[PDB]
Amino acid sequence: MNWTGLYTLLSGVNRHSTAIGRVWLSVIFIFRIMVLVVAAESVWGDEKSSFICNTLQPGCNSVCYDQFFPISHVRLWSLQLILVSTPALLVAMHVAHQQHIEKKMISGTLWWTYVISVVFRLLFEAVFMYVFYLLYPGYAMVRLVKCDVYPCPNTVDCFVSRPTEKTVFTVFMLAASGICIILNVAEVVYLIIRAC
Amino acid sequence: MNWTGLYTLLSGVNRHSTAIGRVWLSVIFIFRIMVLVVAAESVWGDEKSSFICNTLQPGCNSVCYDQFFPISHVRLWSLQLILVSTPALLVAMHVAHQQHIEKKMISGTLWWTYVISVVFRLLFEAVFMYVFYLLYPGYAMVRLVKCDVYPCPNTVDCFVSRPTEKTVFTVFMLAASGICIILNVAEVVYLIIRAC
Ligand SMILES: CC(C)CCC[C@@H](C)[C@H]1CC[C@H]2[C@@H]3CC=C4C[C@@H](O)CC[C@]4(C)[C@H]3CC[C@]12C
Ligand SMILES: CC(C)CCC[C@@H](C)[C@H]1CC[C@H]2[C@@H]3CC=C4C[C@@H](O)CC[C@]4(C)[C@H]3CC[C@]12C
Image (cartoon, rainbow over all chains, first blue to last red; front, top):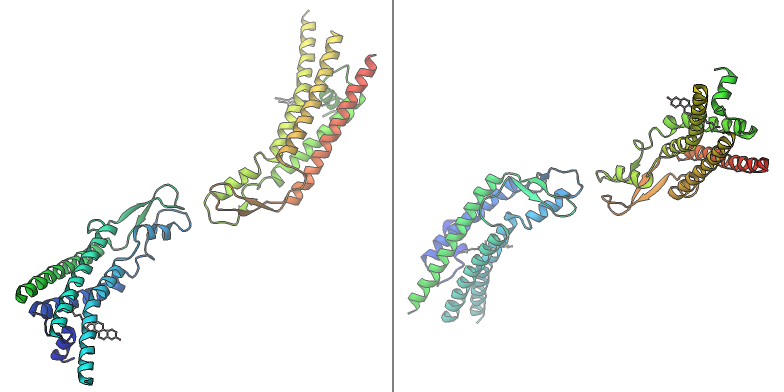
């Protein structure tokens, strides 16, 4: 777990990444993973089991939970991290492949593919930010929700588990994601400026 | 409870009633009352409380019982006895009123009103027989019924209490009612024949 080994691993052995991309982006990425790990099973572990509705209708609990939580926040963030990390993984594999072929026997190609990688990383961050806004308007969760989907008769009151703690972690993850967007834009601008 | 007192009470102090109307009709009427008394609270006492359906839907028990038993057999027979007994009560009151006014101070009127009374008694018997057939086709009740009325989901199985015992008493009451119809027709025919 040598510091130089961890730095080499996270940097992806890329010769075009700048200081921000090799230090700040990696740290914020680690921060999001650690927050997600400590908050996934602990806070969102009983999201559905503890979800109850004030009714005697069989199946109203499950249908109301599905109505109000089409996809859990933890899974949404997990997908966001995987999708955001994919272009970095592709660049690392491409660099390793180039090292392999040159050992068996370019700089502009590496520069261009890195820039495209950062652009796609920024694009994925923006898309997931918009999707999160679309599914869950606002940032705070409420204790009581009004559910009227079939088979629930009329409108029933359903209660969410730990809405305040989930709100706190939602703010943390959203703030970290916003910082990643800002750093990605700065990285793109810095690369373009240095290219001239 | 002197026998002559009971006979005078049941006959209605009528001078036109024949032997069948004063003996057989009264006995069958007493028979129906006694059968109804012993079978009302004992057999049909738990008709709704013991009625259960194989479902978790709240309210499906009550709605299914109402669907399959719009009116209980005991109440239907109770109404039949009251309605059948009404023309006899009217004739008895009219006879008493005539006695009252003559004491204060006709035979054809008494004869005609008695004949009309028997005709209406026969008519009420026939109507209730038809209504019983209309609400409960056949004579035997079944242990299991298929109920699909709202709010019950799809079709549910509901179970009736004491369907065999209720079937036995249904046959008894129906047979007694049929005998009353036959005796009433015989009474009308005999009166018409004797009138000539
Ligand atoms: C600058 C930032 C974005 C760098 C992010 C680096 C991420 C994308 C890289 C760094 C090291 C990578 C890991 C290296 C090895 C493995 C083992 C493999 O069997 C599963 C994937 C897994 C666990 C990789 C997941 C992606 C990973 C964590
Ligand atoms: C030949 C057949 C049909 C005769 C039938 C006689 C029936 C209709 C008559 C005979 C005596 C009557 C009862 C005489 C007195 C009373 C008391 C009153 O406060 C309520 C009704 C009640 C209880 C009457 C109900 C009707 C009754 C039972």
